[PDB]
Structure formats: C-alpha cells, structure tokens
Image (spheres, grey):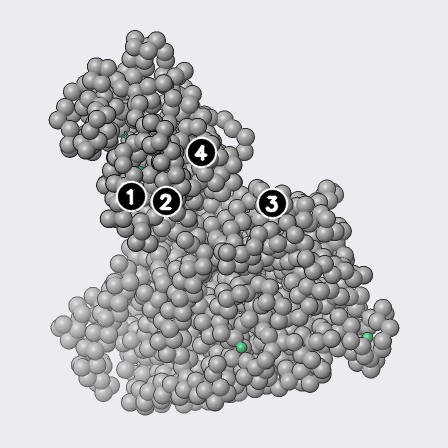
Amino acid sequence: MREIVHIQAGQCGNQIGAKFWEVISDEHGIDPTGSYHGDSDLQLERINVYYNEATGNKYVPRAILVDLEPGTMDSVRSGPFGQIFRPDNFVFGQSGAGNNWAKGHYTEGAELVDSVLDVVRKESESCDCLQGFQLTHSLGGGTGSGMGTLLISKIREEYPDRIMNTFSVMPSPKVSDTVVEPYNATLSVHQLVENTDETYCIDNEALYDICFRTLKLTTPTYGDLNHLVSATMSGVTTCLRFPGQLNADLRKLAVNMVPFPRLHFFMPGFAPLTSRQQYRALTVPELTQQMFDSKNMMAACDPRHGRYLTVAAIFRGRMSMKEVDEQMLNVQNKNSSYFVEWIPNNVKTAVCDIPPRGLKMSATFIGNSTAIQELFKRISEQFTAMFRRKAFLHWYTGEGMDEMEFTEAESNMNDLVSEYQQYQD
Amino acid sequence: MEVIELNKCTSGQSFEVILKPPSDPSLEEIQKKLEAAEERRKYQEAELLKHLAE
Amino acid sequence: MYTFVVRDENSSVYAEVSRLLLATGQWKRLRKDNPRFNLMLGERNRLPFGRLGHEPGLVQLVNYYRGADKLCRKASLVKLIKTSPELSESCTWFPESYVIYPTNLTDEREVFLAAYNRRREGREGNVWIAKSSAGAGILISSEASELLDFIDEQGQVHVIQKYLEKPLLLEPGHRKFDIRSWVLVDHLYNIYLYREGVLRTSSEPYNSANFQDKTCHLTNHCIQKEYSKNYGRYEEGNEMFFEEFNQYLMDALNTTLENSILLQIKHIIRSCLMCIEPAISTKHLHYQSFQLFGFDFMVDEELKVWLIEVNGAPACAQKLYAELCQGIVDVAISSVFPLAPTSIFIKLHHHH
Amino acid sequence: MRECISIHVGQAGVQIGNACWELYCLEHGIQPDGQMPSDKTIGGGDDSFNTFFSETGAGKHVPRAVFVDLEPTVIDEVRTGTYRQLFHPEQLITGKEDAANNYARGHYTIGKEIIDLVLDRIRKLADQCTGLQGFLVFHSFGGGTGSGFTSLLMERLSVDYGKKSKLEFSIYPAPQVSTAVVEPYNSILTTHTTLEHSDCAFMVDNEAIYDICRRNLDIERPTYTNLNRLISQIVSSITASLRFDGALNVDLTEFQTNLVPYPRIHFPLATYAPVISAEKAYHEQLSVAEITNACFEPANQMVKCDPRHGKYMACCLLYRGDVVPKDVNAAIATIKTKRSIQFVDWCPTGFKVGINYQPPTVVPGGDLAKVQRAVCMLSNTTAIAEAWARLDHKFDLMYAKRAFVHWYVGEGMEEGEFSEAREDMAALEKDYEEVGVD
Ligand SMILES: Nc1nc2c(ncn2[C@@H]2O[C@H](COP(=O)(O)OP(=O)(O)OP(=O)(O)O)[C@@H](O)[C@H]2O)c(=O)[nH]1
Ligand SMILES: Nc1ncnc2c1ncn2[C@@H]1O[C@H](COP(=O)(O)OP(=O)(O)CP(=O)(O)O)[C@@H](O)[C@H]1O
Ligand SMILES: Nc1nc2c(ncn2[C@@H]2O[C@H](COP(=O)(O)OP(=O)(O)O)[C@@H](O)[C@H]2O)c(=O)[nH]1
Ligand SMILES: CCNc1ccc(S(C)(=O)=O)cc1F
Ligand SMILES: CCNc1ccc(S(C)(=O)=O)cc1F
Ligand SMILES: [Ca+2]
Ligand SMILES: [Ca+2]
Ligand SMILES: [Ca+2]
Ligand SMILES: [Mg+2]
Ligand SMILES: [Mg+2]
Ligand SMILES: [Mg+2]
C-alpha cells in the first residue's frame, strides 16, 4: 500500500490536474460519483495508490486542490468529475496572485499555506505507507509557481524523507499570458532544483507545436494543450497505477533516473500523436520511432543537441514484448552517440497490458537529457533581457522582494545550465 | 585413471576418480558502523532543517 | 547500420579495413570505449575478451582468436608442437627447437646439449640460431657455448633451433629468402589462404662461412633495407611475388610453385590451425572471432618447406593491401553482418 | 542428522525460494498442506530429508526456512499461495517500504531497524535443531535488500553462529531482466562485505538463465517463474546430497572442502544438462557421455565464460537418474582426450562424483521435460573471474563520474566504502590471475 498524495495549485495546475483525474478515473473504472464499474481486477489492484476507499465502496481521489482565487476550482467542482473530489480538499483564497511569484510565495500565499498543509497532513495520516507527493502547476503564474514552490518547501520540512515529484508547465513567449513569466519561472526553477526529486518539464510551446503541426489543430486552446498533459501524466504513472513485472515506487524510479541530485528534470513524450487516419493500427517499430522523435516530446528541446543520462520507456497494450526489445535495442544501437557511455544499460523498458482509452497500444517516453539545458537557457535569456533594465520589477519589490534575490535566482539557473553542459561532453 | 572411496546405498552411490597426481567484526563493532551511518544521516537531515529554517 | 570500434591505431591492415567499412556507408565507427559495437578491431595485448558478447541484442565480432598466442609465440609454438599428438615431436616440417630459459630465472637446456654433442661427434652440420619474441637481437653460431651465453645476458625466454644450412638460393645473386603467407580464419573456422604471397629475399650473396654478418642470413625487410647495400637490386623492396617466383621455378628447376612448395605450405597451415581448433574455436561461444595470420616459411635446396614462425598481427605487402583487406571485409565481416569472383582466397577444407 | 536453515532475502531470494521448496516437496512426496504419507515416523525422525523439514505433532513437515523482505508484496504471495500451509507466519518477515535498489538503504537505514527481528526468527529455527550445520542464503546482487541487508545478516550470522558454515546462492545482474542501473554498485558493495563471511557461493547469471530459457525451452520472453523453476532444478541438484542418503557433500562443510582450497576464491561455476523443452514432441534421451560432455559447453553454464582459458581447482559431478559409475568413468576418459582441462599444479587432476538414482523431478505443467538422467557439474574455475571483470568495469564507468553516489551517501554511507569495496575486488581479480595465468 504505497500511497501517493496529489496536489494541484493555481489555474494551470488545477485545470491540468482535473483532466488527469478524469483520464485515470476512466482507466480505473471509477465514474464521476466515485463508484467503480470496471470489468478487470487489474483496475483495483493498485487503485489505492491514488484513490481513497470510503464507505459504500466509494473511491475518492487523494487530491488537494489549492488556489488563491475561487474561479478555477469552481469550474472543477462543476466540471465532469467535479463531484468525485473530497469537498474538504478544496483550499482557496479570494485575493488572487496577479501572476506574481512574490504574492504566491511571500504574501498572499503565505496566508493560506498552513490550511493547505492541514489537508496534506490529514491525507498523509490515512496512508498505510506514503510513497510521496506529486504536484501539478505552471511556473509562469503566481499561485502554482510561487505558492506551489512554497508548499513544496514546507512539505519537505515536514516530510524530509518522502519523494517530491512535480509536473511543471514551463512558460513560452509563444503561449504567454503575461510578460513576467520568465521572472516567475526563474524564481521557481531554483526551488525545484533544491526540493524535488523528479520534475517532468512540460513546455507550452512544444504542446502548441504538437497541436498545430502534428495534430493539425488550426487554433489550439488551453484545453487542447491539457489533453496532451493529462495523457502524458497517465503514461508516466502507468508504472504505478497498474500491476506488472515491475515493483517500482517513486524512490526506486528516482534512484535509477537521477544520477546527480540537481539534474532531475525530465523530457516526457508519448506516441501515437494522431490527427483525425486515426483507426489505423500502429506497429511496434512505428511506436518506437515516434516515441524517440523530438516532435513527440513536450520540452521543446532537441535531444540531438545533448546526451541522455537515462531513458525509461513504458509500452501499453497487448503487443510483442519480444518485438519491443528488438526495436528498443534498435534505437540505441543506432544512435548510441546520444547516450552517455558512462552509465551502462541506461535505457530501460516497461510494459503494461492496459492501454489508454481508445488506443490499441501506446508508448510513453521519459528522458533525462542534458539537452534540457536549452529550456533553461531560453528562460535565462528572457529573464536577463528584462532584469538588465529592471523592467516590471516594481510588482515584486512592492511585495517585499529585493533585487538581490533576482540576481541570485539568475546565478542559480546559469549554474544549472553550466552543470548540464559539463555532463554533455 | 583410478577409482577410490566407492560408497553405495539404496538411493545412489558416490566415488572419486583421479586422472593425475599433483605437482571478524564483533557484535559491538557492527553496532558502531550501524550507528555511525545513522549519525551521518541525522547530521545531514539537521543541515537540511537548518537550511529550511533559514 | 553496423557499428565498430578501433582499439589498435597501429594496425595498417585494419586501418584499411576500417577505411573500407566506412566507405560502404553501412558501418559506423564508435568511440573505442563504446560497448554497443558489432565489430571490435581490438588491441594486440590484453584484449578484454571477457567483456564480449554480453550486450543484449548485439551480435559481436572480434578480429582476434583468444588463445591463438600459443601459436604466435616463439616459446609457445615449440611447446605446442612437441606436446601436441597432432603434431608430435617427430614433426617433419618444423626445425629442431628447444625452449631455453636464461639462468637468471620446463627448460630444455640439457636436452639441447645432448642433441648438440651428437651432431658435433657425428661430423654433421651443427649450426644453430637463437631468438626470442622480445626482439626487434638474434645470434647465429656453431658453438653451443656462445648460444647459451647470449641468452643469459638477456632476461627473456629464448629458443634455440637448427639453422637451415642448405637454403634454396635464388639465381642470380646466390641469395636467401623466406615466404610469407597470409591466412584468414573466420568465425566458422574456415581456413582461407590468400592467393597472393610474398618472398622477402636477401639482396646479398649467402655466405655459409661467416655468421657474424647477419645481413645475408636474415631476410627481414627491416634488416635488408637498413643493413644491406644491394637493397632493391633484383626486385623492388626485396619482395618477389608468386608470379615471378613461379616463373623462376619453371625456368630453373623445371617445376611449379604449387607442386614444389605450396602443397607443403597448405599442409602446414592446416596442421597448425586444426591442432588448436578445440582450444580457440568460437563455435558455441557468446561472441565470434576471426583473425589474420602471417605464416613465415623457409625452403631448402631439396624443395622441402620449413615452418619458421606464425605472426598473430602481420603487416601486408604494400601492393596487396587493397585486395586482401577487401577480402577480409568480404569473408570475415560481411559474412556475419551482411550488407544491403573468383575468390582471392584458397579454402583449406578440413574436418572440425 | 544435521539441520540446514535456508534464508531467502529480497524479491529474488523469496521467489527463488518458492520454486525450490515447491520442488523439494515434489521430490520428497510432501503435499502443500505439509503432510507426507511416506514418512512413517509421525512428529519426529532423523531422516536425510529432516535436514530441511521439521515435523509437527500433527505430521506437518515444515521447511527450516525464513523469508525476509523489506516490502510485503512478494512474501504476501507465499502467504496466500499454493504452499501457504507449509510455513507459519513467524517464518515470513516483511517490512513496509523497500531499499529502492540502494545498498546503503538496505544495509544501514532499514537494515539496522529489522536485523534483530530477523535474528530472533532464525534463533527460533535454530532452537529446533540438535546439530545445525549452517545456512543457505538466497539473494540477488542488484537489489537493495538482496545486496545491502544480506551483507548485514551475514556479518551478524558469523557473530551469533561463529562455527557454522554459510553458503550463498547469488543472482548476478543481467540487463535483459532488470530495470535498475545501479546494480554494479550494489553487487560490488555486497561482495566486499560478504566475502569474509561466505564459505561457498554459487553465482547464477540471469543472462545465462535467460538464454537457456530462450534457447532450450523456446520461451521467447521468459518470466520470473520460468527463470526460477530452472534455477531451482540447479539448486536442487546442488542440495540433493544434504536431503538424500549419500556419501558425497553430506554436510555444508564438505562443499568448502571439495570446492574451495583457497578461501577467497569460493565461487564455483555451475553447469547443468540436459534442459529439454516440455513442448517438444519427444526428445531422444541423452546418454551419460552426452550429458557429461554438455558440462563443457558454455551454453549450459550458470555464468557465461570460457573455462578453456582458466585453470580448475576442483570439480564435482552430480548425477541424478539412470547413471552407474562405469558410464561416468568412460565418458570422463573421452572428455580428457578431447577437451582442454587445465588444473592448477598444486591440485590433483580428478573429479568427485555423486550419483542419486532418483532422476530430476519436474513441476507439473512446468517448462522442463522429464529426463531419465541429468548432471550438474560444480567446478572452481579461474574463468569465472570474467564475471568479476565485467561487473568491475561497469562499476568503474559510473564511479569515475560519481554517478548515483549521492543516493548512497544520503543514507549514511561514506564514499570511502565505495573505493574500499572496489579495491577489494581489484585484489580478488589479482588472486584469480595469480592462480590461473602463467
Ligand atoms: N533469477 C531471478 N532474478 C530476480 C528475481 N527477482 C528479481 N531478480 C533480479 O534481482 C535484481 C533486482 O533485485 P531484487 O531482488 O528484485 O530487489 P530486492 O532484493 O527485493 O531489494 P529492493 O531494492 O529493496 O527491492 C535484478 O537483477 C533482477 O533481475 C527472480 O525472481 N529471479
Ligand atoms: N632455423 C633457421 N634457419 C635459417 N634461417 C632462419 C632460421 N630461423 C630464422 N631464420 C631467418 O630469420 C628470419 C626470420 O626471423 P624470425 O621470423 O624468427 O624473427 P621475427 O619474428 O622478428 C621476423 P618476422 O616475425 O617479421 O617474420 C628469416 O628471414 C630467416 O631467414
Ligand atoms: N498547459 C496549460 N498552461 C496553462 C493553463 N493555464 C495557464 N497556463 C500557463 O501557465 C502560466 C500562467 O500561470 P497560471 O496557472 O495561469 O497562474 P496561477 O493561477 O497564479 O498559478 C502561463 O505560462 C500560461 O501559459 C492551462 O490550462 N494549460
Ligand atoms: C485520445 C488519446 N488519449 C491518450 C493517448 C495516450 C495515452 S498514454 C500517454 O499512452 O498513456 C493516454 C491517453 F489518454
Ligand atoms: C507452487 C508455486 N510455485 C511457484 C510460485 C511462485 C514462483 S515466483 C513467481 O517465481 O515467485 C515460483 C514458483 F515455482
Ligand atoms: Ca491579506
Ligand atoms: Ca518422520
Ligand atoms: Ca566466518
Ligand atoms: Mg492565469
Ligand atoms: Mg615475429
Ligand atoms: Mg524488493
């Protein structure tokens, strides 16, 4: 009984979190009112990992919904599976964070953080053996970014030896809400470098390019981007939610994916990504080629610009596990110049029989690549372009922050880039 | 090619063939190791808490 | 896309094989430390055989037979011939040899002397030659006292074998020579003899009354081109190829190279390689081996062929690198990793 | 009669234990409920099989075994499995969360908190023994429990049972059936600290078992059940002498006497034949010479390596089935004149032969076909040092960058223990080379 406590914070965090629970609830046979109606025991095998069992065989997600304004969480409570969440697990304020990291981290967010921890503590106290935590949020806003990283810091203080995992949406000028997103992302990245064991980096630009170019969506919306994220989240957690020839908890994954404590930022992806030629069967070679294709990854980083420290691949559906090993060993033994040669056998493969809704088979990609430094370089350049002129800083100094704290966050991320650069050579 | 020490019983037999002649830490010391590593864990966790308190 | 690594930068043979492999556009060269390779062009010494054939899904091939050193080491070869019933101590095509450890270190010092004293008493030619694998240091003499004293001044194992006092001398010139044969053994243990050989001839007249001057007794290409004054007179680089040497044997001796010499060479090659097959075969192994061998022979005035030594990392004649190297890729590499005639080799069939 | 206590540590140890004790029962005629109709002495007796099974007053034959794992999901299968009735709850020990493939976590962090409980449960079994021989310890190299907690247990067992022999069955890590990347660290760490505590250890390389299952059993993608039922046949061949009437390897001390003349070089190579697919129409039954000759084929070795290029220090031939000495000596003679069997000059060139007339037992519905005769060859070869070289090389590639080291230091281990353990392996490889190479 290795329970995971899920936390979603801010607009982005709660809208992506909502879709996540919608997806896996369908995969586990849980209906919008928390009643099970599946047809396979594999659905209830590891169901307790993400769900609490209440009276009357009801399953309630072990989820905590956090925000500094009520709007987004009112939508969730009115959304498809809104009734499935615990009413007490909604923790929200009224002021908002104004897309301001200082507000989420130091002022508005500090006022609300204790009540969130009360819910976290209450969920942990009912876990037979808490695996760890996962947080969904963006880094470009104020609540998910500023208050999210504050939450992580206080969770680490209270549960120092639990695994802290996040799905972090990185901002992009192409899919931007405000100009201060580089400020908020740079401030959060340092928090994550210190206080998370694994962070799945999701770039909104990659999500846009996939919806536009691959999925042929003329005008992608945030909902379309969230379809990809919820799908990706289902893929990476398949290892944990279903049974198979793998006994892997969050700490075991971290031990085999994170060779150095600060380089724990992953590029995720999956296949297929098909536009509506959607009923065709996808062969294992096709699944494997696409999964390793940069167009199928959501960090907007070209892996051919760096080297893979570790790679994990999860295949779902009834397929040839023999043919999988052949195609996987075909991608490595055909591009070994992109895998570091000083971590033997650093590409691992897992199979899950239960495929996603509406797909015969799929493949989820989780890469720890030094090419992720391109993402942090983009943020750093945008940050510096404004910070050199001290542009928009008054929104932050007005919340008690000082320029010195920005200078240090800038140095911290430039150091992180230099760290990736030395392991790429 | 000699056969020596042939032993036979109801459930089997065994023998030997020669083709050619020839030409700790005490209980206390383990406890110190276990406690030593435990202390280093406490020191590391104290520095983390000191970091978080700052 | 096949992958290979190069771990012997000093190999002229496999430098050409590596050059050809890349030319096909279907082979990729990896860093010498990348374990995910199909083909290893390994180092000469301490090749890590124990690390081959353990990469999942990779069929791996190495250009050296583990254990072939027993044949390509001076001391080992003598021991192999004397102790192997397939070759026996009565082997007729290998000169009488003895393993002699320097006194500053089994050893055959006494056995050698017993045979020596017999020749001295029987008025028979008692001229021997001493050598070792730690040489560029060779000594030819008729007195046993000088031979042994030379080994003690050194610190490595030596071997003393009978010196062919009646070598076949080419005319004109009255000069010595030795024959080099290249042999390729593939993963299936087929023995391929390169159709092209080379005679490394001495450009000096053979003199049997003065072994102090080793320029007319040693036919090594480095000694003739460094200590000989008539280098390149009769043939370019003191290298006569089979076509010329065969024509000579017809005009002079009224015989062919095939009948008078090549039959014995093929027999000697088969005997040596078949003998060690059970010890070095990779038939039922987790990795596959092949290797190119350089056999060195001597011919006496009776047209009897003598085996001198076997080299496990031979160089090739400049004029024969292209043909032979391409041949290595065809039968040894592409036979295991096929790409997307009239063979240059002569298959010496045998029972496995 | 002298008792043997089996200890199964971590996932690999526990699941291999399931296959072995299943096979033991089928070999001795014990039912899943523990009853043994052939045993005419009810609630007692000192028969050969009593070295591995105790007896209750009600006639239940209870394995002298302890299953230990830091996480409960693997042992919970035993608690509800076919043979749930064989063991009582005190024999199955499970913690809450595992070692996460982290040697330091299993040895120090978690190991320190449960080691006393495990010893207490072992002490209970020992108290039922009137003449305990020692322990058989099953575990993986790569698992954080199999590596880290086993080494701690071995240290304590040497303290509490200083005069008792300890043998190992260790699973050597192979990438084809592992999703871990740090197993070379765990293997070297546990071998260093366990070396001075194990009298004899049988390494099984999963790569070898995997290939035998694909090659001989035509299993395209073998599972843990396929691998473990094959491993348990080899384990049974090795331990059959302790459970059946005989005169060769009759007690644990004899394994070191017959296979380990030098204490540190205590890793015999195991070779087994024949392995025939049950799905085959009907295989031609192999002869003594043919199965004996197969003991010198690299393809049926528990660890892939080339014994032609090592030296033998000892050699046992363990036959089960229709085998008489006349046929063994005849086959051995033929193998000397064909194979390259080089013994060390300070060891006699000879074989100790054991014959058990009961042929190999096969689990119903399993993958292995019933054979009229089989052999397991135990030979102490320097060639097995290839497995140390391979493993040590993978260690060096990662440790040069200090990859993953922080996970171990974070659990209270000092980095110095890495290099200390690696230097011990470098000396172990030197010892092998001094004995084998000229
Ligand atoms: N032959 C065989 N090998 C196994 C089996 N189970 C695991 N392994 C191998 O053991 C290694 C993994 O270690 P485990 O034994 O599973 O881990 P553990 O001992 O339970 O320790 P933890 O890290 O706490 O889980 C890998 O090399 C696996 O291939 C098994 O049932 N049979
Ligand atoms: N028993 C013998 N009788 C006559 N000549 C001999 C001889 N042993 C060696 N030689 C001469 O020595 C030369 C070969 O020497 P050897 O091969 O033993 O040394 P080496 O191995 O350093 C040269 P390589 O390996 O390149 O052929 C030949 O040219 C031959 O003429
Ligand atoms: N993928 C995705 N990104 C979003 C969504 N909503 C906001 N974002 C991104 O998140 C950042 C704004 O943060 P937001 O979550 O709205 O602020 P917060 O509520 O204060 O945490 C910008 O980079 C947006 O592009 C969403 O629903 N999906
Ligand atoms: C409509 C497509 N949905 C979907 C696709 C893939 C996966 S995945 C990453 O393979 O788990 C999950 C999904 F929900
Ligand atoms: C009679 C039960 N036998 C058995 C059970 C489990 C395993 S397992 C999956 O390898 O743990 C092997 C077995 F042989
Ligand atoms: Ca306020
Ligand atoms: Ca009884
Ligand atoms: Ca001891
Ligand atoms: Mg917003
Ligand atoms: Mg030479
Ligand atoms: Mg485990």
Q: Chain of mark 1?
A: C
Circles 2 and 1, Cβ within 8 Å, touching? The answer is yes
Identify residue type, mark 1. Answer: Leu
Give the Cα separation between the discs numbered 3 and 2. 34 Å
Q: Which residue is mark 2?
A: C109
Circles 1 and 3, Cβ within 8 Å, touching? The answer is no
Does ligand 2 reach within 8 Å of label 1's beta carbon?
no
As drawn, the label of residue D369 is: none
As drawn, the label of residue D335 is: 3
* Nearest to viewer (mark 3 / mark 2): 2
* Mark 2: secondary structure: helix
Give the Cα separation between the discs numbered 4 and 3. 22 Å
Furthest toward the front, the residue is: C121
In the image, B31 versus A13, the foreground residue is: B31
Q: Which residue is mark 4?
A: C272
Of the numbered discs 2 and 4, the one sitting upstream in the chain is 2
Residue D232, picture quadrant:
bottom right
Give the Cα separation between the discs numbered 4 and 1. 29 Å
Identify residue type, mark 2. Answer: Arg
Circles 2 and 4, Cβ within 8 Å, touching? The answer is no
* Nearest to viewer (mark 2 / mark 4): 2
Identify residue type, mark 3. Answer: Ile
Q: For this view, does A274 lie left or right of residue A1?
A: left
Residue C171, picture quadrant:
top left
